[PDB]
Image (spheres, coloured by chain):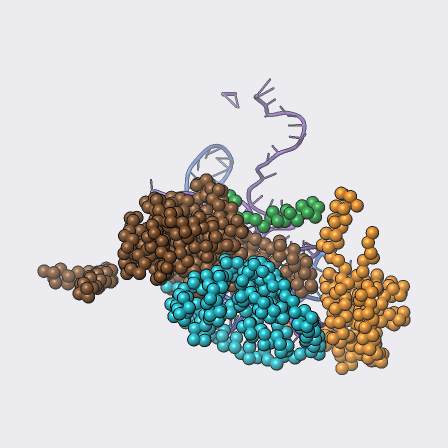
Chain colours: A green, B brown, C orange, D cyan, E purple, F blue
Amino acid sequence: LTSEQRAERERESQSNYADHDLWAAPAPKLPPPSH
Amino acid sequence: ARVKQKGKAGAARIYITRNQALKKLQLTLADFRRICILKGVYPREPKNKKKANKGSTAPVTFYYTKDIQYLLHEPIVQKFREYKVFARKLSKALGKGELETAKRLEARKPTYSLDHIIKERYPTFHDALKDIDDALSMLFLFSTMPVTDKIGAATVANCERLCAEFQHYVIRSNSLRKAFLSIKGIYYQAEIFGEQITWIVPYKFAQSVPTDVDFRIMHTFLEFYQALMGFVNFKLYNTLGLRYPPKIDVAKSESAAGLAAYELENTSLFSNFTFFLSREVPRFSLEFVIRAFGGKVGWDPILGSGSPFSESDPVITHHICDRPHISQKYEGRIYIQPQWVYDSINKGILERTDLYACGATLPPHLSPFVEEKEAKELSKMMMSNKQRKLYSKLKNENSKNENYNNALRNRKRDIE
Amino acid sequence: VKWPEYIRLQRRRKILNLRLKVPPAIAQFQKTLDKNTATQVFKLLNKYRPETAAEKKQRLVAEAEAVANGKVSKKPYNVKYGLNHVVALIEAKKAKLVLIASDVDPIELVVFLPALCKKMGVPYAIVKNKARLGTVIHQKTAAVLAVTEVREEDKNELASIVSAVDANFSAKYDESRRKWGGGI
Amino acid sequence: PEVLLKKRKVNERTRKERVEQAIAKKEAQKKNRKETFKRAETFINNYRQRERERIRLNRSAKNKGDIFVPDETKLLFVIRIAGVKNMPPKIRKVLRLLRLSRINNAVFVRNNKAVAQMLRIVEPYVMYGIPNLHSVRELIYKRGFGKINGQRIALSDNALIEEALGKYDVISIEDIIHEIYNVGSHFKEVTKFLWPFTLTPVKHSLMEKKVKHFNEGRKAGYCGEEINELIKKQV
RNA sequence: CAGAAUCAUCGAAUCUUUGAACGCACGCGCCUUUGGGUUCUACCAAAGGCAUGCCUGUUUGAGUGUCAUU
RNA sequence: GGACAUGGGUUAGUCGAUCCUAAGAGAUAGGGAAGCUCCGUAUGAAAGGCACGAUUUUUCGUGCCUAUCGAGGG
């Protein structure tokens, strides 16, 4: 890849924010509600 | 067979101390906590302590051996060492003066993704919705904190991005149910997919850091939750048909536009109502709460651009304002206090405006989440394990407060 | 404190060098360039560092794409390193200043260098440690560096340094280089 | 189905003992890092800077009594990038006149002929630009500090703002930002009350904690709206 | 005696305990994962592992070995 | 018949071995030897683990202690 494609592909990297869906140890005992 | 030795099975075998768990995994304490934070790991107190400690007595934290052996094969543990490798190579480059291999190394710094952590920790979406309340409280808390050396700026940007997208979701889904107020902040409460979600929003304020919180821990939790938020919101938007992540306009966002930057390309309690936001109120909380119930919302331009209304438009049904003085008071925009809105939210009923009007006494707020001698002396002595103490603990603090607050009503009527 | 067999080996060897009657040719490699001139020497040298294998490629791709689409230079100026390459340069009198690593492991390599550089009249100095000379050229270690030719902009700086090495290294010592070292 | 969370296994007794020992060891180190040497080179460098600075003042004041007067903003934002040891007497007073007595201090200034002139005098030491409403909002709401009775007081209560600024129709934090961005009549009083902010450069990634004299590449002079982005990174 | 073959051919496999013989000895352990039970913090089973000398590389280091850092 | 022919028979948590060492054998660290091999086992060996800690620069800091086979022992 020449200088520019590797540069623009470098920008297209470093980007991974919620692209796919995963969903196709007791409970932490949630804190008591407001009093 | 031989005489089996002491502590070769049972509670002296499964329960393994923290120091042993360190040398079994070959980790330092700080890394061990990190993999304990990321995974679901927590001490478990053995029933028989000195039995479980090879006859010792000193107080020591214990873990399940089965739990530790799971951490032995965790693939991310390697990415901890690869960063220990990376740090030394970047120190090497700066030492020799390679200000370029330093720049390329930092570009190719090792990464780990919590995708398999989330799947193995929360299998079902309902599992996530149950154990996500602290995540909402966490991320929302951080979006109003000045960026420090311990917490990077981009992490704050991740909080603000993920915080707003969730606010957009609830307004779009109309899933907001209650919104309680307190000196802690604005205790929000919604429900999604049947499960109930609750959190607390800090007052957006020029706070101070107490210089005793160990920010290292708090940094890993963000590195955990900010992974959770992306994938939880992703399913919600796909379920709602929205394209995740919603697009954000930089120019709008740098004008304090709040949710206006992002485009999403008794639910009707305030459907037929138009509200205006004056320049003294918590716009961030009020924008979210009113639009959750169909309220048409405009705000003062000094709070941010993107206001659909101006000041002069009389279509506003209620011009909310807590300022003690209103020089240019309008008509048709009956002026009430913000406590009116949350009271309407809790009750799901249009509250009375004039009692909450400007200069009026504030009504109190309600939290929406909230022979005898012989028969009492025989079981106190003629029984063994003494669960009779349950009354002395459970009933005592309930009886005293019930007696106390019942006397409040009588004493307050006397005052009147 | 029972030392390891190799800690004992390291330290006994160090003590041995300071005790024996070191020959003059090996004795000169113990009295070296001072610290102030050492950083000044390397201030210049770190201008003429040869480009790394990372830079030598990123540059050559730029020419390749220029040729691949549609399409000459000036002599590359940098520092000369390598024992055979440098030893040739002194003999060919192409070297302006030679910097000799003070602690080369088989001392046979550089033991003849001060005599040869004196013979051809090349101003030389024995800079402390090879790893300093290694980092200038992007290597683990350099037995010897040499400045052969600098741009006109820095021609004055090199001349200033050369007179310092004369005054601080060769003007000083000189006679002490002809005495058997060690024996302490 | 009841997972009782017990008390921490942390032994808060030893934790604070370690903390106190940590503080005890830290103060000794500061009291030990004393009276370092100074080379003959830095004495030169100060002199070269001082004559370089002094000549700049003469050319700036004499024959150059002209200012380009940045327009379309009544309010500017100025921060001090760096200072020179053995400060020139003129700059030493002027920086105090702008309340920038210490480095990394952030102060708002109303744009006019006079202020821009003093900024032009101290230009090589300050990075100044035009903040946007949002950038000013986070500054007050995350780093705003008050001067109540003359101590270092955080703007933690709106009651304090009303108490000290009631007679100038300033009641709340939101009143402060609206006044400052609009530069009203009480702009001078509010700016007098406001304690200067401290935008110390942030060091998060490993490369920054190691490069020497890292200041995020802060230049000196006009930066337009880049100061907004710098604030966004900084706040 | 009561697609065959006590067949040929041979590119796919199986190849018990050993033996240079290699977890340790001539029976006893450790390590990682998986399973079982009308018994589940116990017990058991199973599969896969653990010889030394050397070479390249890797990671973690030691050194009053050499030296640098206003 | 102890011959061959044809079958059957030794059941263990508690009895012994397996568990241990003695004199010595003895691998290793080393060192000899052209070499098969030899000497050496406390030897100028970096020869085994314990605890502590809101997590420490989100790169481990601080503190303590110093082989093996071989039958009377169980």
> Eyeballing the image, is C161 above or below D132?
below
User: In the rendered image, which quarter is residue B324 located in?
Assistant: bottom left
Kindly identify the residue that appears in the image at 55 percent across and 57 percent down.
B80
Image-based side of B207 in relation to D91, left or right: left
Kindly identify the residue that appears in the image at 58 percent across and 67 percent down.
D113
Give the image location of residue C12, x and y in percent: 71, 74
User: In the rendered image, which quarter is residue C8 located in?
Assistant: bottom right
Give the image location of residue B279, x and y in percent: 41, 58
Q: In front: F30, or C30?
A: C30
Q: In front: C166, or B268?
A: B268
User: In the rendered image, which quarter is residue C102 located in?
Assistant: bottom right
Kindly identify the residue that appears in the image at 34 percent across and 44 percent down.
B272
Q: In front: C34, or B76?
A: C34
Image-based side of C122 in relation to D77, left or right: right
Kindly identify the residue that appears in the image at 12 percent across and 63 percent down.
B373
> Eyeballing the image, is B98 above or below B73?
below
Give the image location of residue B411, x and y in percent: 19, 65
How many numbered circles does the render carry? 0
Determine if residue D24 is in view: yes
Give the image location of residue D122, x and y in percent: 62, 70
Residue at the outermost left position = B371
> Eyeballing the image, is E23 above or below C32?
above
